[PDB]
Length: 93
Image 1 (cartoon, helix red, strand yellow):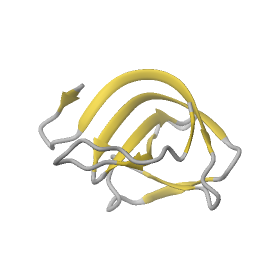
Image 2 (tube, rainbow, N blue to C red):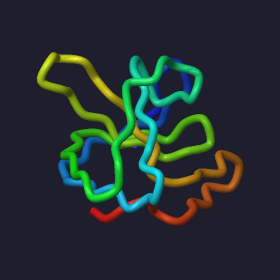
Image 3 (cartoon, rainbow, N blue to C red):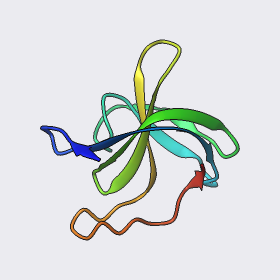
Image 4 (tube, rainbow, N blue to C red):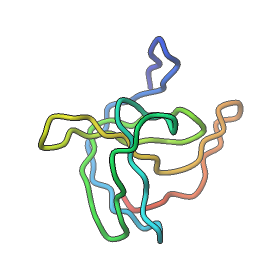
């Protein structure tokens, strides 16, 4: 794990994620923060391959690049910054 200037915990990791959340997962642009503009919604059953994992804004995120070259961040589980406790995974890896 490594932390950048903004306090975003990131780590390299190459794996695939399949969304199992009933109502899908909302994706964001720019970074792993709920306040960033929405990039779409990944619905149940859909799978993506991420190249980096982040811990920020009370969640664990996975990121990847789209065909268009934009980086998209997706939350995958809750994260308590003060204790490090992580919640249920919203999909399979």
